[PDB]
Image (cartoon, coloured by chain):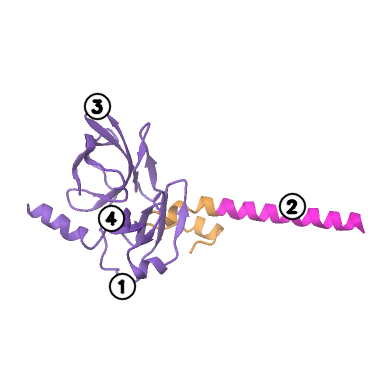
Chain colours: A orange, B purple
Amino acid sequence: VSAVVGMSLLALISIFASCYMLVAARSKCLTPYALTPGAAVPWTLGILCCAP
Amino acid sequence: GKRERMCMKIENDCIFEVKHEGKVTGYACLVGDKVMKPAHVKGVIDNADLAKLAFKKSSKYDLECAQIPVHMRSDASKYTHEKPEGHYNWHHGAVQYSGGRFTIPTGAGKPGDSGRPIFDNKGRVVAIVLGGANEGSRTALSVVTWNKDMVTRVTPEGSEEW
């Protein structure tokens, strides 16, 4: 029981950390385009990441 | 003269002010279809409608941006991206630009005056003042540009954050 609980917890924290850091990478790649007045994100980068 | 009067005429409607403890401590501007607000200054914008609006933050570039609603759409600042060399207007005198650097005469920039945009000869806005560093009778400027699609910060050594 203890081993299963520990393994599940470790898998969950690994998945969460990976997802959060990938989200951070997205948000840091697409952060300057929201600050530039006018202009627009390229369609390719706006497809490989969801760009509002 | 007339140019000073027209500069004041725009400034009475385009540039806003932030306040804290009953004292104004920063100026926010509306450029293009966004808002610029240097991120070192904290306070409540002296406008009910803009304050309720949700912001965005990036401490790398020391600015806060957003999207304007549709009832100040006409009150734009006519952005531009070209940087020929010459002289450029500002609320605190005429600033000249040469060698990729902005220069001001000594102590014409005051503490707490950050956020005021610069104007070119055609009146378009080219950068936002963030801070300054002095050398001799001239003081260098730390401003953020709008080169193409990516904003870029340029800062001299020992810059004092206004």
Q: Which residues are magenta?
A: A1-26
Residue B23 image offset from top left, x and y in percent: 32, 55
> Where is mark 2, residue-wise?
A14
Point out the frontmost of discs 3 and 4.
Answer: 3
> Where is mark 3, residue-wise?
B136
Please report, as a chain letter, where disc 3 is located: B
Q: Earlier in the sequence, mark 1 or mark 3?
A: 1
Residue A47 image offset from top left, x and y in percent: 53, 60
Q: Are marks 3 and 4 on the same chain?
A: yes
- Left of A47 or right of it: where is B133? left
Residue B110 image offset from top left, x and y in percent: 26, 43
**Label annotation for residue B79:** 4
Secondary structure, mark 2, is: helix
Q: CA distance from mark 1 to mark 2?
A: 47 Å
**Label annotation for residue B47:** none
Q: CA distance from mark 2 to mark 4?
A: 45 Å
Asked if disc 4 and disc 1 are in contact, CB closer than 8 Å, the reply is no
The amino acid pointed to by label 3 is Gly
Secondary structure, mark 3, is: loop
The amino acid pointed to by label 1 is His
Q: CA distance from mark 3 to mark 2?
A: 56 Å
Secondary structure, mark 1, is: loop
Q: Earlier in the sequence, mark 4 or mark 1?
A: 1
Q: Residue furthest front?
A: B21
Point out the frontmost of discs 4 and 1.
Answer: 1
Instruction: Give B146 or B102, whichever is nearer the viewer.
Output: B102
Q: Residue furthest left?
A: B1
Task: Name the residue rendered at 33%, 41% in the picture.
Answer: B131
